[PDB]
Amino acid sequence: MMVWTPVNNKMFETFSYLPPLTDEQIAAQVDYIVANGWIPCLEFAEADKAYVSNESAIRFGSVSCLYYDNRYWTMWKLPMFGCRDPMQVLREIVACTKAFPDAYVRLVAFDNQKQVQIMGFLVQRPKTARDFQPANKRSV
Amino acid sequence: MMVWTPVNNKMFETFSYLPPLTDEQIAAQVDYIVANGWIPCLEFAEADKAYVSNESAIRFGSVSCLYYDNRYWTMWKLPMFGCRDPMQVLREIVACTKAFPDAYVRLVAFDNQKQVQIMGFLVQRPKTARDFQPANKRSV
Amino acid sequence: MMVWTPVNNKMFETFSYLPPLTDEQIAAQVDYIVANGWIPCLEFAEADKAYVSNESAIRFGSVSCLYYDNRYWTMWKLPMFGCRDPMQVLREIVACTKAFPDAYVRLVAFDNQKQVQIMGFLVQRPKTARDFQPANKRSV
Amino acid sequence: MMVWTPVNNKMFETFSYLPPLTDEQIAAQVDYIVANGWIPCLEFAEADKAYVSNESAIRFGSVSCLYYDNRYWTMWKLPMFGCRDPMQVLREIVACTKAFPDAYVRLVAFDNQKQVQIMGFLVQRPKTARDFQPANKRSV
Image (cartoon, rainbow over all chains, first blue to last red; front, side, top):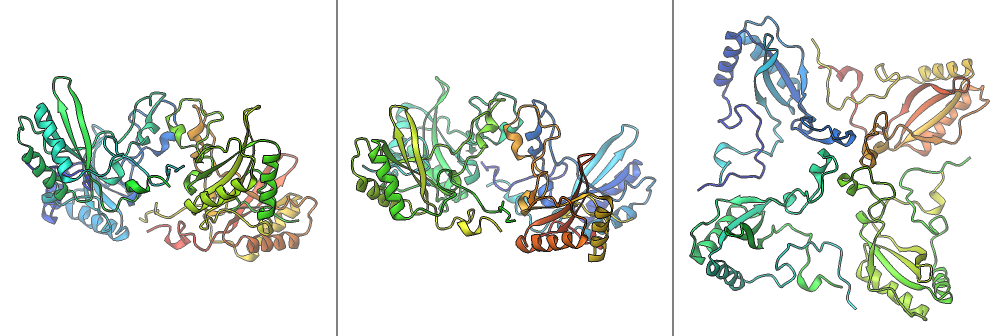
């Protein structure tokens, strides 16, 4: 029996339970976005603004249900409408991470027919981050 | 007249007002669990999650009565159902404290007829803890 | 025109706007307690528990009116019932401040006919305190 | 496409999106106050009291609408009623910033006919402030 650690074991939604995505694996996800005609977009956040929190609820009556702070991140430029080139997306990942080397960065994609985000995964975390585990240290 | 110190004098429920339990005294408590046919279990928590707090109440209407965060700790493996061997319990204490040397660890036991925890006491605190006093410094 | 500074200028209720009390001035206040047959008592608090605050109100409905945390401090021993000796009070000030050299300490007195505290002033603040001004620096 | 940075990019209301005001530009704003017969005044705040916050709302029922802490700053002396001399205002700026070199300081002016503040801009921030960007680093 192995024990799932509660300490410094924060996750990041889709694909965070898999081994970290290689460049080849990221390119494959980008190909999938393009193949489906979805709209790629990059979003970023400083460390303090990365995980869901409750601070604004101090201002509320009994209306906190499904309200959380830090769901919104900051948009990198604009969604890439009309993008049919995976290399353009990869170049924007490089540009965003270069401009904000200490930020969390996630790649998302939108479907304008359902009008909903249809994919999303983390592509950068700050080097100072100490609040997560390697796959093989997730259980002790 | 001696004065009970209010400063860095945090307690830990059952047996925290006695001298710290020796290995022999811990073994005697484990024998008592086994003699009564209760279910031993270990639970642990990082320092920040060890004592009762109020943070989630920011999300509440007027319903905080008997709500506290940090009552639940994290289960080490599973409760030791069918355990009739005190040495097995003592070995799990060693294993748990080895895997989490910086955590608070408590031994508990369950009665499945009353369906309630029937015993409980601290077996480890982190070495960095400075929020408690030795027996002879609890009063000044 | 001089300007009353808002920065690090915390006060401590009765007598805090006067020059700090000398040992002779403290002795005179003790004489007043004894002369009136009031009950002297010492109370103390660590720095974080010294000034009025709001933290418990996170648990409340709309009932915070005239509720503040940190109004209660910790009693040194017991109120000195029957005390007819000013020197006994001065000795307890020495004893309390010796036991808690980093605490805020205040001398209070009770009237049991009105059943209310009838005097009170600070007799010690921690040496590390940086949130108050000497008299000649309260205006700039 | 340049990206407006969300990190350490705090603003300070009127004129904060322009290049920092030169001494000549400040003098011109003061001339404008005097020309219109408005009442000049200086206000200041320590760093922790400079930006709007919500802390007091812990005490509230459902009445936080348009309540914020830190809207009030501290008045330097009194508003300069009857002041028709721009050099007097500039000397008070010097005097205030000298007395409080580590404070935020803003120049304001009042109209007593409308009874409202009619102009306002920051004239000093503490040298330790690291939550703002120079004009050429606001976008990346």
